[PDB]
Image (tube, rainbow, N blue to C red):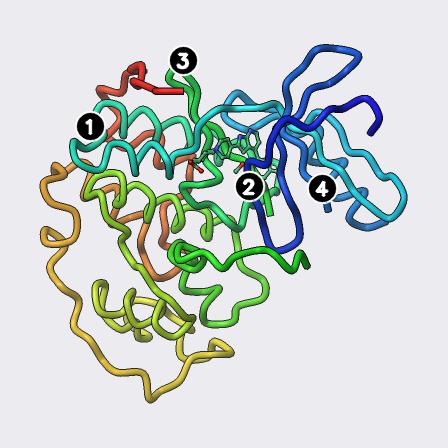
Amino acid sequence: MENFQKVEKIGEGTYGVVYKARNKLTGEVVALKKISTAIREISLLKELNHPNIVKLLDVIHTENKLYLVFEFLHQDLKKFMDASALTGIPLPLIKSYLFQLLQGLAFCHSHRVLHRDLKPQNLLINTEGAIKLADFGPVRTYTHEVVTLWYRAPEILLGCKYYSTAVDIWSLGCIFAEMVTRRALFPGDSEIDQLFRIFRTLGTPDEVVWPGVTSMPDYKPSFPKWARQDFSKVVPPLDEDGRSLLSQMLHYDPNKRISAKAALAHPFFQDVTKPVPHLRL
Ligand SMILES: COc1ccc(F)cc1-c1ccnc2[nH]c(C3=CCN([C@H]4CC[C@H](CC(=O)O)CC4)CC3)cc12
């Protein structure tokens, strides 16, 4: 740790604080997260190297603290969306970012690694048009964030403890809808409000669309029964290729939900390109 100099605080989580830091004996600018089974599960993340995954450079265990050293990126997608809120991110750039994240997930998922907590703030962007997955899934000062449950898959909210890679596809579908509309798809402020916001839009799930849903640990037969609203209302003015892909990413049944690998073949990406975003750093 004596090999690093703090420059500023760049973030916070339930169990850690993140700083922008400088490596004294290499000159590298990194992001440093300060926090036996964990030491091994995080050492496996060091081998999960892909152009669309923020590089985990090192793991340092020093005097009852764990430090994670990552490659530094200047902006996150949440800030870029907040900065593009009045104009909207151009469709070619939304498509490029979605494609790149599906490539990163196809990679993680093939190595049996789930992210579990995809949200705009852990999607980092650079000046080259790249987007990368960060912070693969207590400090008393951590401030509760409005967006915390907004991207949670319904199986997680329904108490499934052995959920699959499909939970990441759900979170990315929510992010895709948000880039298009400039508003959060399911802005829930509690587990039940999050569940009911999903139900209000996609219809209350039942055994027809999600076999086994009524046997989930937190499923209650007393949940109000909302009709599925027609999908053209959910992400206007996104085209039919985009709406079709999004509907597949938001299927209730995790087994019907499109995989990252199949999503890359979707006709929506036939004209995918890699535009350069305009970033003000
Ligand atoms: C999500 O990423 C992580 C999570 C855990 C972790 F351990 C490391 C990383 C991580 C890895 C690599 N590179 C990174 N870069 C960054 C940020 C760079 C600048 N962001 C800005 C500051 C200014 C704000 C506006 C204002 O406050 O005025 C608008 C947002 C914050 C986040 C975080 C981060």
Q: Secondary structure at mark 1?
A: helix
Q: Give the distance between the C-alpha atoms of the residues marked 4 and 3, in whole angstroms.
A: 28 Å
Residue 34: assigned label: 4
Q: Give the distance between the C-alpha atoms of the residues marked 3 and 1, in whole angstroms.
A: 17 Å
Q: Amino acid at mark 1?
A: Leu
Number of labels in the image equals 4
- For label 1, the residue is 91
Residue 128: assigned label: 3
Pair 3/1: label in front? 3
Q: Amino acid at mark 3?
A: Glu
Residue shown at the point (9%, 40%) measured from the top left: 237
In the rendered structure, which disc, 4 or 3, sits on the residue that comes first in sequence? 4
| The C terminus lies in quadrant | top left
- Whether disc 4's CB lies below 8 Å from ligand 1 is answered no
In the rendered structure, which disc, 4 or 2, sits on the residue that comes first in sequence? 2
272 horizontally vs 124: left or right: left
Q: Amino acid at mark 2?
A: Gly
In the rendered structure, which disc, 1 or 4, sits on the residue that comes first in sequence? 4
Q: Secondary structure at mark 2?
A: strand
| Residue 131 percent location from the top left of the image | 43, 26
Residue shown at the point (38%, 43%) measured from the top left: 172
Q: Give the distance between the C-alpha atoms of the residues marked 1 and 4, in whole angstroms.
A: 37 Å
- Whether disc 2's CB lies below 8 Å from ligand 1 is answered yes
Residue shown at the point (24%, 32%) measured from the top left: 84
Image height of 15 relative to 216, above or below: above
Q: Give the distance between the C-alpha atoms of the residues marked 1 and 2, in whole angstroms.
A: 29 Å
Residue 11: assigned label: 2
